[PDB]
Image (cartoon, rainbow, N blue to C red):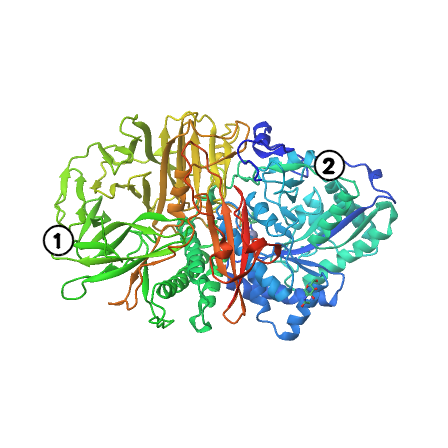
Amino acid sequence: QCQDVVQDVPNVDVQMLELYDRMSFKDIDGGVWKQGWNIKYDPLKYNAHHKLKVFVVPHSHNDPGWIQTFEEYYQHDTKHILSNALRHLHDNPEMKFIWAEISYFARFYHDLGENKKLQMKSIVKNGQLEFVTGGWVMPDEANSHWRNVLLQLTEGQTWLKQFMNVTPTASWAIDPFGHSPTMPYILQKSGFKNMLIQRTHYSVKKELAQQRQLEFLWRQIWDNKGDTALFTHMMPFYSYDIPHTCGPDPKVCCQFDFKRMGSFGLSCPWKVPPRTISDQNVAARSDLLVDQWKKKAELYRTNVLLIPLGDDFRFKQNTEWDVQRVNYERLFEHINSQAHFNVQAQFGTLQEYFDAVHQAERAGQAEFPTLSGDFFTYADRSDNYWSGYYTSRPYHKRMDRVLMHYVRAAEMLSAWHSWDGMARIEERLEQARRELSLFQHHDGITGTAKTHVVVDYEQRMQEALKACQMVMQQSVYRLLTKPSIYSPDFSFSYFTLDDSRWPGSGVEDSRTTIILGEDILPSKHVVMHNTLPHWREQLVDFYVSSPFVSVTDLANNPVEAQVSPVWSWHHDTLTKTIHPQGSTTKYRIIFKARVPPMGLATYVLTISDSKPEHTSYASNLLLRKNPTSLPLGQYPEDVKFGDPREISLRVGNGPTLAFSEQGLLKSIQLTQDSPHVPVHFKFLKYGVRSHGDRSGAYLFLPNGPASPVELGQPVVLVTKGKLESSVSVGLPSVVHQTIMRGGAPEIRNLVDIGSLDNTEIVMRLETHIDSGDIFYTDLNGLQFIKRRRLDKLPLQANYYPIPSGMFIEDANTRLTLLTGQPLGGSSLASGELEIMQDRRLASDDERGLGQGVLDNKPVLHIYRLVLEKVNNCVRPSKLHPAGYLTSAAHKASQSLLDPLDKFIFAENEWIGAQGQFGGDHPSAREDLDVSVMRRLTKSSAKTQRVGYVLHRTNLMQCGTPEEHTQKLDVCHLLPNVARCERTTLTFLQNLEHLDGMVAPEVCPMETAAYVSSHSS
Ligand SMILES: CC(C)(C)c1ccc(C(=O)C[C@@H]2CC[C@@H](O)[C@@H]3[C@H](O)[C@H](O)CN23)cc1
Ligand SMILES: *[C@@H]1O[C@H](CO)[C@@H](O)[C@H](O)[C@H]1NC(C)=O
Ligand SMILES: [Zn+2]
């Protein structure tokens, strides 16, 4: 059956949390290998019967945006690199080259004439040009959601299968800023056999090199058996450039980068240039080079050595191809003919290296260690920890999560039908997938690109959101209209989307008001979509032009509703206060929507002359000295005023929350009899150092612990309703809101750092939970990993990515904070959690960007805050490196990432309207998700195919009885199934033909893919 992911601590040779606890991290001068030691080798190790096999692997690192946009780099650099690679590889049969970024390759290939397309296919088929990874990009591993890592992998590999007839099984990741085990998890389930990484902490490189543990079988932290393991090669040195890839001494290796002699505008900072290889110098030059190679080889276990040969946007000019190739050819000819070296060297590809390593392994020449854990937080030198980019450009980090959900919902809603080509569904979805995939780049979501490049990514994502909206609204109109009435114009807007949290109140005025009136329109249809495979209830809200509005379902049953004002916050430059203003013509109506699994539900909003029977009205209380009136038009309850004071609120039977006179949470009481548990929100600021290294887009280099934000006497607004209550406060740089709907509260921060140079704003929670030095953070929204604060490392080293959540706990109590956007955070003291909101930095931090971060804009960050008793939960033992969410915390995360979608009918009358779609869909167990539903065939295919990715998380057992749910068989969701296959996660290879056309559910922590085939 399924592996137990909770109760069995895996036995591994290297466990990264344990390694961290033991290591001293001393930054000593190691000599020419500045962060290592003087490597020694026995010249007699290699001989006639045991030679060192060396593969020199030419490469070119091509960023899809960084200092220039994607299109700018394509025009100025990449198109020339690819054109000259085609010519030079065609003309020189022994030359080799690897390529990673399929976004660029697809852009190039589609512009080639047919003759050159054929030449290109031939150099791929014969093994000269080899694709590595084959993703659209080389993604960030810290901020990216696993769903989007899979999306971009699939986009690149699907293109490669169709046009190049290849599927890479070796991955190459030389530039992301630290590395996540989410990568081998996805890769191993997508047919991969090997992977390579580079950016790991210099102290980790030294420690693993000393033990020859730089090649390892990387398994997941919970995996007892080892079925998830993927062979991994970690590079040993400071960079992927030529000076740091031939061996330990960059002053020597730089002399073998033949682009650095002068005419290309490049030089060697160690002050010894390369020299052209000649018959008079080749013996001395070979002496030097082979010595570097044999030193590098000492760090690894086989007689097969990998020597990358490349750098950023290399291999651009014909003269560069010639200068590298001819000089290396002269070296190979000498070395391979001199028996005393006992070396055979040649150009190679990445797969050729790994194939030779495993041949050596099978011959019994080496065994490899097992490893679990991650490689965050990275430092490349001294105290320069790269935790800044966990937060940089937070507006676009939030946008990533919004678009993630819109892509999923658009692909799912449109998958139910086959569409005519005239509907442009495939076209719009391909655009949306490619723009989101592009943004996964390690200069996209990371917030590490130049200002105009960030603007390009934003514009691309906005076009993607519009594409998703078009596809979603056409799909809803088709799914909910009587078939013999349905009459689509594929360019028309039948519905508009309403989104309450993006761009958000105070960020953009983007939401449409539903206009009703006795002399214009009495009522309006709205529709909710639920992408999750279980029945779901959620409060939804709409703007309406009257407070006298009632809600009905499509059987005309009344639905209880609440009306509240529309409140907007203003920085009043006259009075120098931050305060709310209410609308006198627009109101919010709020009601509970109930929606089938993967389904739709229709409701109707109707105006009346006076207060409706089933609609209530919130009270409003403004707490401030020196109040002035706040008129609200037709709204039936007058606003009340008071001096600042402590207050308490409770919605339904849920928790009771207490707030300070500054409008910030101070305690949570779970039930009527229970204690008021101290839980305090506080805002603080970090600064920048006045001497030494400065914080920038990459680096977090604080000038000591954070200092409290001076709050003054802020204005607090309290709204109290039967369905929803809230407390909002206008603080310097942040409008902070706590919202209560009967369960764990929602927190929203409208963050505007303004002109506060050299400031990072942090949100901290203070509790009395006895967590000590332990906390938990997630990796890519997929898994929670145990962290240990280490006082032997600086503050910035204790910051980790918070891509979707974090928690602290003791024997009895847990506090979990879930996020709707990736940000950086930590627990710097027992009982605390903190998460960075935004950062504005005037200085460049010397990693090539050449600017600070001064382009901040208002962003609405969203969260859920879950306080729970955990004394009854079955948790992992003290030595287990993982943690797991409870049911309530998991559902709270889903409420942020995949909320209900809301659609407003755009015309006056919807002819043929229906009340529901998906009432007969199975309601699956709460830990199971249909992460992806995607139709894989166009309408002309006789046999239609639909792909599903199914993910089961693992939730803690805490004594809540399980109610029976229904089995979900994705292969029977569409009618007329003829075949069901288990596939790789990219859908590109069939792995299992399934009995009775039934797709089995997956085990906890597992992800599987299935494709159903249908007669059409
Ligand atoms: C010359 C100097 C300014 C001191 C410098 C230093 C370091 C780097 C990198 O680490 C390589 C960087 C790391 C950050 C990342 O944003 C960039 C781009 O992705 C590009 O591919 C090279 N990458 C580059 C330049
Ligand atoms: C694609 O690759 C396979 C495996 O090498 C080969 O059998 C097939 O003929 C190739 N398809 C082509 C060249 O169209
Ligand atoms: Zn890069």
Marker disc for residue 634: 1
Q: Position of residue 138 (x, y in %)?
A: 56, 53
Q: Is residue 601 left or right of residue 849?
A: left
As drawn, 199 above or below 941:
above
As drawn, 824 above or below 474:
above
How many marks overall? 2
Label 2 Cα crowd, 10 Å radius (few <14 / some 14-19 / many 20+):
some
Label 1 Cα crowd, 10 Å radius (few <14 / some 14-19 / many 20+):
some
Taking the spot 50% from the left edge, 57% from the top edge, the residue there is 438
Q: Say which quarter of the image contains residue 18.
A: top right
Q: Residue extending furthest front?
A: 996
Discs 1, 2 touching: Cβ within 8 Å: no
Q: Say which quarter of the image contains residue 78.
A: bottom right
Q: Secondary structure at mark 2?
A: loop
Question: Which of labels 1 and 2 is toward the front?
Answer: 1
Kindly tell me whether residue 69 is visible in this rendering: no
Residue occupied by mark 2: 39
Quadrant containing the N terminus is: top right
Three-letter amino acid code at disc 1? Gln
Q: Position of residue 110 (x, y in %)?
A: 57, 70
Depth check, front residue: 475 or 232: 475
